[PDB]
Length: 61
Image (cartoon, rainbow, N blue to C red):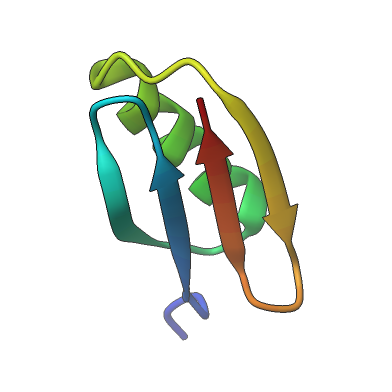
């Protein structure tokens, strides 16, 4: 079988970057790593939340 993948969402409230993006991953920690890399790549340095009920991460600057 192929692994079950979940679509995770990132809500971004940055100084210059704002909106939402998504990633697919087998677990939340993998999605978190992808989103933290994306934020780093775009110069976003904020604080984060993760809601396991909605599979949504939020970062605010």
